[PDB]
Image 1 (cartoon, rainbow over the protein chains, first blue to last red):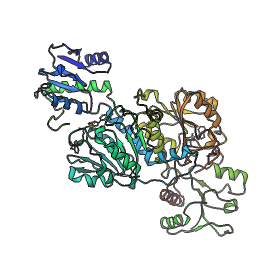
Image 2: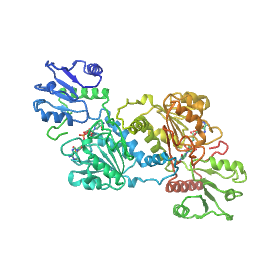
Image 3: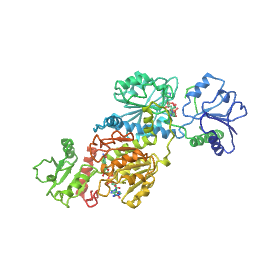
Image 4: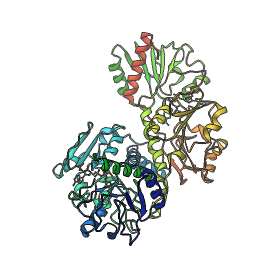
Length: 310
Length: 310
Ligand SMILES: NC(=O)c1ccc[n+]([C@@H]2O[C@H](COP(=O)([O-])OP(=O)(O)OC[C@H]3O[C@@H](n4cnc5c(N)ncnc54)[C@H](OP(=O)(O)O)[C@@H]3O)[C@@H](O)[C@H]2O)c1
Ligand SMILES: NC(=O)c1ccc[n+]([C@@H]2O[C@H](COP(=O)([O-])OP(=O)(O)OC[C@H]3O[C@@H](n4cnc5c(N)ncnc54)[C@H](OP(=O)(O)O)[C@@H]3O)[C@@H](O)[C@H]2O)c1
């Protein structure tokens, strides 16, 4: 088989050599402009139109968990990927654990009031504070997918009450499952901590706005791990300033890098990470891609729903 | 039976009523000065000499995990507790989980470089940083007891390499056990993170000094969860200033409250909590005390070694 690989910043030769070892019958090459030679599979991140247009590929593997970029490119350029070509994304491949690390650390940070103790330390002021209790710290996960379920699983270990929101009902024994826009208000009413693990789709853009935030309990916390477009940043800032939201830790933003003029940078209740919550682990991605191609070849169960948008 | 209770700041009537429900045959009273009436068990925190002196008690229950205070008082006042009287302390009773919450949150915080991102956020500066790897983040637990083992167990969940140090060899399958002063240098050589869960005894006072810190890997982290006397604070500050130690989170100090003149308060790589790492959970302490008395009465297995000092 023939595999073409494109990624704008990764160690390309590293990936080619790992793919060749994992798929020893494959001829793997880096795609450059002008390469119209035959290919069976394409591995891509932010590919240019010309790399895929007209190609009757057996599959395309997008090298990320999110697919809002490629799907929006395919809508602007319908000629880019034939409907006959299945599109795959990276499910977990190590990003599950990374989301768990981030969420557990920061949920515990807030639960143990390390944010309040830091404020007090800034004034060299010693004062034990009342303990918080699990019953008042229900954690709601917006998005109940590959990453949402991993984050829910790790927080259940700590015995926090847990609820999740998605389009379809979930069956996780200790997690209350809310589904659809018609159940979102009830979902939000109890979320002391709100963790966002939704995909970017037309249906979820701007969903964390003033009406959503007002339905949370007072003194809530927001952990945005998903996409910046999900949050109306001026609405979040107003809820932080009014005390509705006690703290927000944000990995993603409407414009990235976050412009220095944004009030989020210097706001005392905001913590910023520069879109680093979960990165693809190359060796796990190669194992997942190699395994998927083998299953495709054998006609076994294994994918992105372009109509659905994620 | 007769139980006398003394605690200088807890909700005394709450404890008396919970002890009466858990031990319905018991007459429970708060000890005041002048009460020389008979008693079978004493429940105490920082008791005055007069409460125990001359009393042939069946047992004394110290209402804490640490016992350096009462043991030092007994050495200064040998007449206070007859050698015939067994002394018990609170083992876990909820402090296990609290130590796990603290340690897991902060270990993950450091592993994911939230301390570096915070420094960068202070300047509104956006910059992804290289990932750290588990193989470079061995965690060493100084003290391998009730709380040490719980902290080790929770960090193994995250697949960090783990080692522990104590007087006697441990058998935890995935944790390398170092024992005695003669093995401490080898123990320390690999500790990217050093977590202190030792008791305060004459043998461990000042153990985290300049010679210990210099044996750690560069860029190490210190989490002092145990006693302030374990750390020579000026030696820690010199190791922070030289870059040997990248970060220190401290819950305890040689003088408490930490005096405002201490350079630890404003040091950029130090995080301070005001001795709040793990507090006794009253209902769990009552359950443990009630269960222990029942086992004593039935002649079953169940205690502080005064000769040993912890
Ligand atoms: N560094 C980073 O910040 C980083 C890294 C990786 C990924 N991510 C983000 O995390 C996202 C999730 O990854 P994943 O693998 O967990 O995705 P996934 O497996 O597709 O899960 C998506 C979840 O969102 C739900 N959802 C989608 N549209 C919805 C709507 N309109 N209403 C309610 N729920 C809806 C789905 O519900 P159903 O279960 O009913 O379908 C599903 O539970 C990605 O889209 C990406 O944006 C961020
Ligand atoms: N808020 C707080 O900060 C807070 C709250 C509760 C407790 N604590 C602290 O945590 C301590 C530990 O509690 P615990 O219940 O885990 O105590 P523990 O069960 O008695 O464990 C003590 C451990 O320290 C080791 N040890 C004692 N002396 C030693 C020496 N000279 N060299 C090497 N190892 C030595 C013991 O080794 P062996 O196993 O060989 O005997 C044992 O593993 C308490 O003493 C207290 O100071 C702090």
